[PDB]
Length: 52
Length: 50
Image (cartoon, rainbow over all chains, first blue to last red; front, side, top):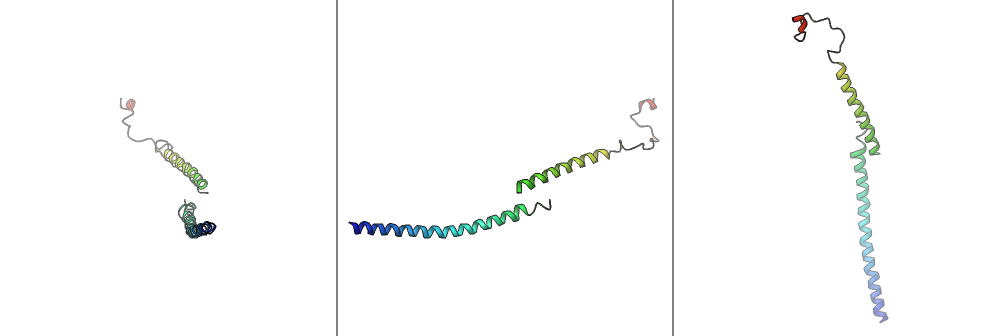
């Protein structure tokens, strides 16, 4: 039973490792998107004010 | 920063608009000094016509 439980325990640790790996890959893409969004805001909304 | 700059532009714009309105008013021909009386009697001068 212990082996089965611990086999299941290992399965849980592996299923979690899979989720974390997927989660960290998504965060990397989100950071890249946030950097572009901030740059786009400065170019489209702030830089045009000095001329006005 | 965007909100603050926006407020300054609005204040300058309102002041600019009000100035243009006043200049337009002051440039009215009827307010401008003693143009040499008109040689012709104005239609509104009923006394001279009479």
